[PDB]
Amino acid sequence: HMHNYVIIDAFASVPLEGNPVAVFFDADDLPPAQMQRIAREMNLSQSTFVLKPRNGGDALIRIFTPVNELPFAGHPLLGTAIALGAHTDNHRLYLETQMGTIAFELERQNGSVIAASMDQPIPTWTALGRDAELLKALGISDSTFPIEIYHNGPRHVFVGLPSIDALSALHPDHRALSNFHDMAINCFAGAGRRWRSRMFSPAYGVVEDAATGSAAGPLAIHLARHGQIEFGQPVEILQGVEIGRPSLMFAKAEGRAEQLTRVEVSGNGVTFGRGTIVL
Amino acid sequence: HMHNYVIIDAFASVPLEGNPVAVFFDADDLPPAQMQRIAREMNLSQSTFVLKPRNGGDALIRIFTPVNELPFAGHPLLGTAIALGAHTDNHRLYLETQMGTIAFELERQNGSVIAASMDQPIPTWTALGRDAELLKALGISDSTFPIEIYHNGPRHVFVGLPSIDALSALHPDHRALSNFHDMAINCFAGAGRRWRSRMFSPAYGVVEDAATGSAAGPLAIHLARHGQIEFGQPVEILQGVEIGRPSLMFAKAEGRAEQLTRVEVSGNGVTFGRGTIVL
Ligand SMILES: CCO[C@@H]1C=CC=C(C(=O)[O-])[C@H]1[NH3+]
Ligand SMILES: CCO[C@@H]1C=CC=C(C(=O)[O-])[C@H]1[NH3+]
Image (cartoon, rainbow over all chains, first blue to last red; front, side, top):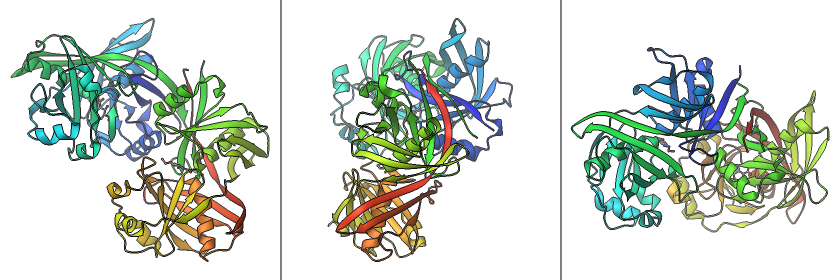
């Protein structure tokens, strides 16, 4: 009774950039309570567990924070797909989750998976309706674009800043942000294809997140809806620069606001470490 | 350029109990900034790095949280000593730290180090002087014994409860506790040789700690000073039960309050995992 694991830095091509996730293989012998205890033991923002598939996919993936199981998270699933590429020749990988089966395209160089693209759940969205409270918490007077909250498992609010330097200058009051339950606050700035983001979430137990993969799809939708890109055009989103964990996420939303057909998010991943646990 | 590491559960004899620390070997090639980045990457409460000695010890140990270096911490040094026992036959280990050289006795069974005892810095102490504020934050009316704050690197406040069940019933207001800077709050209950503890510290970035090894020595002093044990008598301190990380710490203080000669803390440790990182 031992399990091998890898630590993947997701949305990075260099170790110690991007956002880490520990991926545990051959986890079918672990009861869920033990998966939870292991995720707590590692204390990474998420640990994932690779299980035999039950509905025709390649594998079933369970995602745990140190305190609870999650239905969906982008960077942990990206890292899981990249890690599993070391163990399959498949060009595509179908990972079963609580959101259904998530399709991944694996990208390789000489047998090593260096990147992947995923099709995300199509989000829903509406106005947050707490704008002055949120802006006060962030320390700014206004957003550029409408402050809207998106749902694809987790919930993501988007607040637009007028320049990248204004984004980097943010020093939010995290106590005030803690009154925004069950959501993450994503502040963004940029133009055209290239955007910068910073994510803050007391609700999700993070002062500032390096790479919020489940926010990248919704941000592409947000930018297309508010006229900064078209549906069908990709954006490059660079997150985590200010905290020294630069993370590059690519995202594209196809269709139109009223009839979205696909939400794609991709990025590189690199192995930081590999190990074995004693149970 | 790779480094091996182990995850040791300190103050435990069973994996997933006690308090984890990652121990990185052969770290002399790592600049301190990189040690800090690695400790952040792992996100364990502490990671330690094993370096060549500079003042006649066996090794020099650097202790990092995800955000800063620490001069002293008990469970990380305990785990480091136990981990290093896999690589030496020595009965005693002298580990250089910012507090000076810390002497460890290693305890083995068939070549495996299963426990260790350390001589801790002798603490200083005084009344906290914020009793009503602290008791309000904890949700209780009074302490049994004087509320005093001890210093041996970190700072530890001790608040006594009238029964173990009263200790387990505590649900502190962690926002109110956050006004207690640069210290940990240790609540305790028990009798004779056997004590229970719970530690809370927003200042040290933990809602509730499993095993606060640097608090065990000061608690023995506290109990001897306030007449519950004698100087020279050991106590058993069980921490972390309520959070499912039961941790057993043993402590003894020799001398008298005005002239302490030794503060000893010991416990078991077990390997949870072993790995290698790519830099
Ligand atoms: C600790 C915060 O972790 C985030 C929580 C929910 C969604 C994520 C993601 O989608 O990558 C995570 N990055
Ligand atoms: C995250 C909190 O970690 C504690 C910090 C300071 C001292 C410790 C110890 O002495 O074992 C640590 N347990």
